[PDB]
Length: 263
Image 1 (spheres, helix red, strand yellow):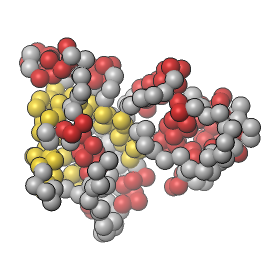
Image 2 (cartoon, one colour):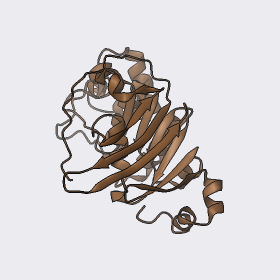
Image 3 (cartoon, rainbow, N blue to C red):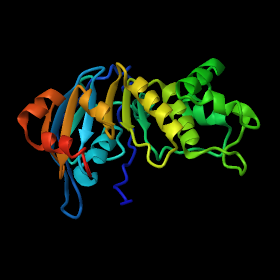
């Protein structure tokens, strides 16, 4: 719950590319006012369609890394490139419309279910695309059991929407966005079993053939990733495929046998 630095949103880049899903971190460093070295010297190349699974403790740097990718945190040194374009040369709106951020802290608004899915830049989406997104999030059927269906306004009492139903509405927003880059924290903490089942399926379907950086919680996400990056104290400890990292018989191997406890 620490406060972070506040970026200035100097939207000095004017490029409006169609992102293809290549990402490169080039010697990225993140140093704080108090001397903390949050990220040391981080380099990683991600090709279009790849999933990179981040593994590591809560303070290891995973959140700071992906925040830098959406310019929610600035970099102390180094560069980030999207399809070989420096990220700061891209118009911020263009960047943010093309990167989906999915996690348990996504905001639900006291607005219709429709507006919660067709939110913001997607406010004028076609009616059938909102339904398709809700079906892909396994939310359409329960939305149509709400008192006023898609016109039901969140934030009231008596809606009977569980946490796992609410989280599926938020996932539908990300699916509608259909972004070439997905930043996923696949947490399903405190949700009911059935919601967890459908959410895991929606997450696997969202990662399919799409550039994804995932803060992993499930073994399948880690083992099937194109690259696994084990972070500790802001540094890459090791990186590679599941097969390569097992063969090293090192940090990842030990973590795998401990079911990634605390990582």
